[PDB]
Image (cartoon, helix red, strand yellow):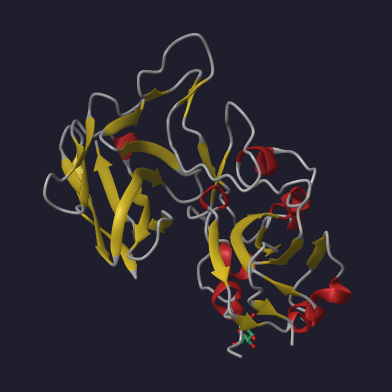
Amino acid sequence: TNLCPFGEVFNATRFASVYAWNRKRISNCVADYSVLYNSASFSTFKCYGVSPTKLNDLCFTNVYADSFVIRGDEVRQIAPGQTGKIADYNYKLPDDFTGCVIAWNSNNLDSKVGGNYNYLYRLFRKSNLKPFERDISTEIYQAGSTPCNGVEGFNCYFPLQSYGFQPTNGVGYQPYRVVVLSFELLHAPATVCGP
Amino acid sequence: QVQLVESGGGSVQAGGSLRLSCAASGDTGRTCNLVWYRQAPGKELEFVSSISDGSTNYAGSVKGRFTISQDNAKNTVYLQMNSLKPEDTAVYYCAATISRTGSLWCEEYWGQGTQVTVSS
Ligand SMILES: *[C@@H]1O[C@H](CO)[C@@H](O)[C@H](O)[C@H]1NC(C)=O
């Protein structure tokens, strides 16, 4: 009965840029999801394919915890069936997702005077990501008929852009930390259970 | 336990040169890629150059003047900056995606920045 190490995910001092989202595998442990659900710190707590009322009564083969920073008005893209720059090019949930999405405002940690440089997102991609796909490449995006030949400029775009979070931004443009919990059930022994 | 440490910034006269270094240390595994960016305060972070598995790219404004290279024997990438111009003044940052021992996931790390100031 070791307790699941969710603190390492939720309380990490730095989070990943969404294009380079992080994942931690959680297994062989007991989780009290009510602590997360009841925390006043989280302004989003939305589950799909499972009801919150059941989280402490179920066992799963593995839980994955993916985490990253996006801007507030993009949190809505972290849900099945959604679209936009984040869902299309950065982090994509599947239609049949079973899991929960948890988010909170991180303006106090993730903005900087003069604009934070640390948090980037992919702005251009030739096709949409498949669910749970990850793209950390930085090839020049060729927007037109002229080959870019490894040089950024007209019609030749570097594909990642900084959010530039500044503490004075409006709330929709402020950083939010996001943790996505996936509940995986395989034909294998369950290892992560509620209490 | 991976860290990126920059070195090499400073003040130079227009036309001069500097060489920046971005050195990875700790429980490093494979580097998937590495990007040099620059930002002056309040301005949007700007792409400068990147390198991945030997392929390189550059901002149009620095192509021909700056060269990115991977050290043939060290966990370090250099940015050689020649023919410097006042417009090159900024804090330069490296960012890399690197897996750590025990993992196949390349995770993002950032250097601490180095000021470059070019005066006319
Ligand atoms: C994060 O840290 C706080 C304060 O140390 C702690 O009370 C909380 O349980 C942690 N969150 C987790 C483990 O999800």
